[PDB]
Length: 251
Ligand SMILES: N[C@@H](Cn1ccc(=O)n(Cc2ccccc2C(=O)O)c1=O)C(=O)O
Ligand SMILES: [Cl-]
Image (spheres, rainbow, N blue to C red):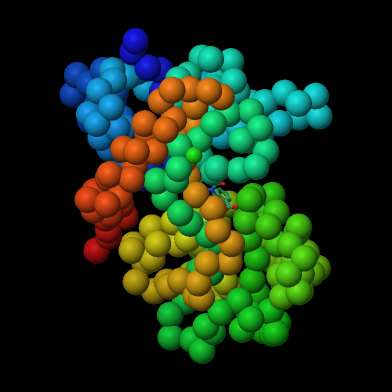
């Protein structure tokens, strides 16, 4: 059985290789998730075929309980595994299984260096520095559903200034931090990726929430626990660290 692996284009997890050489099948791709998949294949001993998810979505549910994205590929048994920066969540666990996480991350703050600002409190108790998040993304949702006193104030701040505090996308948000007295709330993985490449930017404070990326499988898949095992081995031997450094390290 050659396993079908659903995944999604997302830098630096999954990208097309910058090459016109005759590369076919799995060889067309590179990135952290491709390296992880290669290690998993070698530990477990499986053949695999990487397939980009056709609708280009991670996976969410409609009012009819119908799913899309990589999650739907697994549910429909059109993929054996999903190896991507796919968040392990309560709603997804109802319909698919996940290995234990290969990466743990959380919302944090991206801002300029050399400022007194040190945490989320330093932003909430002031208005001279604008702060927001990518509109309609996981990060904004967190602040909109959070009952944590301090994050309720931040959302009340971001929302009252929806037009200029909530950006269109990461690229826009990053440029906004670079070109104005602005702080962007974004996942720690992305902040790390951007700060490695912009010496003028830095992360502020610690993790605001916590979640992990896991390998998705259909419910009952006999590969799930084996993949967890392999992940732990990689973690313990320092391979996940070197895999992360390989892709994240900048100049
Ligand atoms: N992990 C998410 C998808 N995903 C993946 C990488 C990632 O950086 N983000 C964060 C993100 C991407 C684009 C725009 C906004 C945001 C955000 O942090 O809100 C994700 O939401 C999921 O599983 O649905
Ligand atoms: Cl588990």
